[PDB]
Image (cartoon, grey):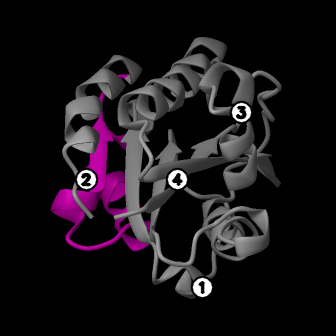
Amino acid sequence: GNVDLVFLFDGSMSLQPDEFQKILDFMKDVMKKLSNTSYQFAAVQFSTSYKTEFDFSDYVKWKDPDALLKHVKHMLLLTNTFGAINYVATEVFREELGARPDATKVLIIITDGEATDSGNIDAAKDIIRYIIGIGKHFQTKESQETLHKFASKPASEFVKILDTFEKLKDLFTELQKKIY
């Protein structure tokens, strides 16, 4: 079956330059490793504001992860996760931007801290949502639990807590093995 997968990646000022680059490299590696007719991809950077770095039609045009993320600039502002998820639901998953009506909608949200906004993500309810919380800001159970509201259930499947950015590599096999 077809899968339309969006990477939604944190560009806040909490992220150090090497860490942000490891996130970009992870997205490129996932695209290279999942690449096949079934998958198409989009990517959105979120911080204070939201930017579609490439949409599904851009992916179809270029099919080159290096090219697709070449123009990304680290935003270095806040962490407005609620609005980011809603932005994906309403502004990225659109047929006019290359989204396929028959495809399973998937989000991989990548963040290094707690949200700086609030509200709800009801608009994104029909999207299968993974969230990856990385690093020292998720050392407490309480901080980890804040990510559950963003992800699909069960949290034991959909919420991934990684203690270091080096652990992103350990998610490749898992993501490759998903059958939606």
Let me know if residue 108 is in the magenta part. no
Let me know if residue 139 is in the magenta part. yes
Distance (Cα) linking label 2 and label 1: 27 Å
- Report whether 116 appears left or right of 36: right
Residue 126 in view in this figure? yes
Q: Are marks 3 and 1 in contact (CB under 8 Å)?
A: no
Residue that numbered label 3 is attached to:
62
The image's mark for residue 114 is 4
Frontmost of labels 2 and 1 is 1
The image's mark for residue 92 is none
Distance (Cα) linking label 3 and label 2: 41 Å
- The image position of residue 33, as x and y in percent, is 37, 29
Q: Are marks 2 and 1 in contact (CB under 8 Å)?
A: no
Q: In terms of depth relative to the viewer, which is nearer, 125 or 176?
A: 176
For marks 2 and 4 on the same chain, the one whose residue lies earlier in the sequence: 4
For marks 2 and 1 on the same chain, the one whose residue lies earlier in the sequence: 1
For marks 4 and 1 on the same chain, the one whose residue lies earlier in the sequence: 4
Name the residue: 58% across, 26% down: 24
Frontmost of labels 4 and 1 is 1
Residue that numbered label 2 is attached to:
141
Amino acid type for the residue under numbered disc 2: Lys
**Which residues lie in the magenta part?**
138-164
Amino acid type for the residue under numbered disc 3: Trp
For marks 3 and 4 on the same chain, the one whose residue lies earlier in the sequence: 3
Residue that numbered label 1 is attached to:
123
Amino acid type for the residue under numbered disc 1: Ala
Name the residue: 49% across, 44% down: 110
Name the residue: 58% across, 70% down: 100
Q: Secondary structure at mark 2?
A: helix
Frontmost of labels 3 and 1 is 3
